[PDB]
Image (cartoon, coloured by chain):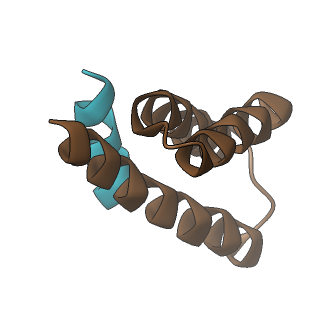
Amino acid sequence: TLQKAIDLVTKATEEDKAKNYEEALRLYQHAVEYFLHAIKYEAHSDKAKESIRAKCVQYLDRAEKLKDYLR
Amino acid sequence: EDQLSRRLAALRN
């Protein structure tokens, strides 16, 4: 799930750079969604969970901004 | 976590 979480967000970032909000959104929601599921299942501590949460919360905001841009 | 977790679930669905 870790690789899928990173590989997903990684593809979303590149997409956003190539004027691909659509492909970037699907990859973003897929990455963040997989990240959260990984935390609820397994985690290290509040510290680590925080770093993963902040990165997810920020990624989620960008998603809604993309879907809204085209919508 | 529930904040973004909820808004995220709505995005996909």
Rendered image quadrant of residue A45: bottom right
Residue in view at x 28 percent, y 49 percent: A64
* Percent coordinates x, y for residue A67 in the rendering: 27, 39
Toward the bottom, the furthest residue is: A47
Is residue A59 rendered to the left or right of residue A55?
left
Chain B colour in the picture: cyan
Return the x and y of residue A17 as percentages of the image width and height: 60, 51
Q: Residue at position x 24%, y 21% from top?
A: B13
Outermost residue, front direction?
A: A19
**Residue in the image at 45% along x and 63% along y:** A57
Q: Colour of chain A?
A: brown
Residue at position x 73%, y 43% from top? A10
Q: Is residue B2 above or below residue A25?
A: below
Q: Is residue A38 left or right of residue B10?
A: right
Q: Quadrant of the C terminus of chain A?
A: top left
Say left or right for A12 vs A23.
right
